[PDB]
Structures are given as structure tokens and as C-alpha cells.
Figure 1 (cartoon, one colour):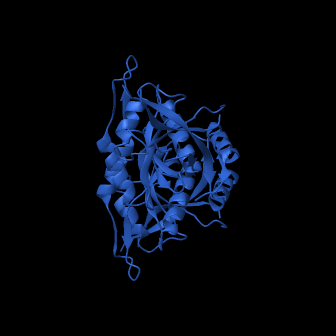
Figure 2 (spheres, one colour):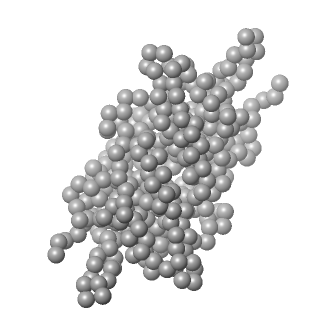
Figure 3 (cartoon, chains in turn purple, yellow):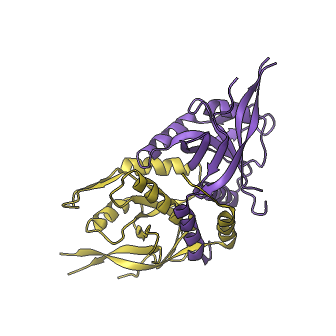
Length: 179
Length: 179
């Protein structure tokens, strides 16, 4: 029985910023709920490089979250859109804003595995005063009625140097207000 | 004859980061050319708040840039996609990575004005060691065979405080490598 296909997840700053920003922006218009999205990137050495992301319409019943939907058409359409403009990136997994694993995450991940068999879920912490921004997981089968569970994958916010200096330069740029 | 509809453009950090990141990422796979995209946001007080953006497929002939195309279907489709997930944002204009105005920018802007009559163009400086990240423009008519020209609009990287602390927190998070 083979080890994980992914042993580390590097989430690029833009992804974190995107996800946190999107989450806070929907929060201002009354978002009551976690955000779910797709992660795009590339794999090198059992290391997953998460370079991009996009939120997807997602609903889940707040009484029984076995009732949940993601439009895979939306995700495929968005991904196709992205492919037209972006440097080669692949669906490498998905994200949600957590804060923790939800019961239906295994099922969501099973839908995501349609697009990436070694789908990694990253919970992205969007709480301002939290953490360790990312927590990565890969679904793992536990044989007994065989069961699926998330196994933690080492994950970090990571950036190539030129990319971090771009972020550093970003922060030096900023003026307040705002609305 | 009335003054500009927009007198200041606040570009949010995520937009700059997105645009610079996208540009550098396509650069690594041999992008030879400026990136063009759409800006989304909202207007308050002749102040345009640019909160989001997306690149669009764009081609322009390098001999005669009167030959250029943007798929407005792509832009409408992407915008509709975004509307499904995002807090209310509108097409408020467009961007390109410059470094300077191109001859066909007035024409591009005319296409963008289909979506936003008071379209603002923002040239986003993606050069690492440059600047003043943004330069905003609004097309203005000069009556004589009446002519269109870009007028500079005050523009800044701007963030609400909570949003800047999120960026500050981003930079404190980052690890090197990278690839």
C-alpha cells in the first residue's frame, strides 16, 4: 500500500489573499457560511504548489450537510476560462475557509477527485486574529466497510523570492481607506 | 460640458498582486506581451474602488495594433461567473500591464465602455524594480473631427485597514521556495 502522492503543500500568497479577501467581501454583504473553491497548481516532488484558486458556488444544508452541492459545470467552466489566460496550472485540489473539517468534506473531495485523483483539501484560515493560515489534507482510505478520512499534509504559505519581494512591495505601496 | 465621472481610483492590493502574479507566471512560460484584463469594483464619490480583476484573452498585432481583439464573450462569461460568487462588483474598467499607453487603448476602452460608460483604464506596473504601481486614465473627448484621448485619473493602491492588516499578515506568513 503506497504512501501519499502529496506530502507537502505550498500555498502561494495570492491564493491566501484571494481567499481571505473574497471571504471578507462576501461577509460584508451577509455571508453566513464557509467559502469553497478549487485550487490550481502543479506538483513537483510529492510537493504540491498551489498557485491559484477560485471560489465556486457551494451550498450545504445547515441541518444535514450530507445535503450539499457544488456546480462542477461552474468549476469546469472557470477552470477552462483560466486555462485560456493562465500559465499551465491544473486542478490540484480544493479549499474551504473552515475553520475546521466539515462532515461532508470527504464527499466534496470525492467530487473534486474527478478532476484530480490526488486532490488536496486546504482549509484556509480567514480569521484576522488566528494559525497558521493553511491546513492541508488528503483523503486516505482506511480498510476495515472501507472508510475515507483526511490525513494532514504539511502545508505552508510559500513564495519564490521574486514573488515574496512582489508581496513585500505590495505592502509598502498601500494607502488607507478603504471603502 | 461636465467634469469626469471618476476623479480617483483606488486599486486594492489583491488586484495588483493578482495582475503582477499572473503576468510573472505567464512570463515564465514565454509571455512576450502586455496583459489586458477587466477591473471590477464600485464607485462612491467620483472615487472608483477597484476590488477585483481578471485577465482576458487579448491579441494585438505587433506591427499595427489597430488589429487587436478581446473576446467580450469571455469577459461577459467571466464576469457572470464572478457574479455568482462574489459580493456585488461591477465592471468599472480595465487594465493592462503597459508599461505605457498603447495606440489601441482608446479603441479597447471603447469596447470596455460597452460594459461601463465611465470605464477607467489602469496601467498596472508589473516591473519588480519600478513607479507607482498604478496609473489610471479615463477617455475624454476632445472636440475640434472629434477625438478621444486618455486623461490621467489620480490612482492609489488603497485598502481598508482590516484589509491592509490582512496583507501585513500575509507577508509575515511567507516561506521561501518557490517553484
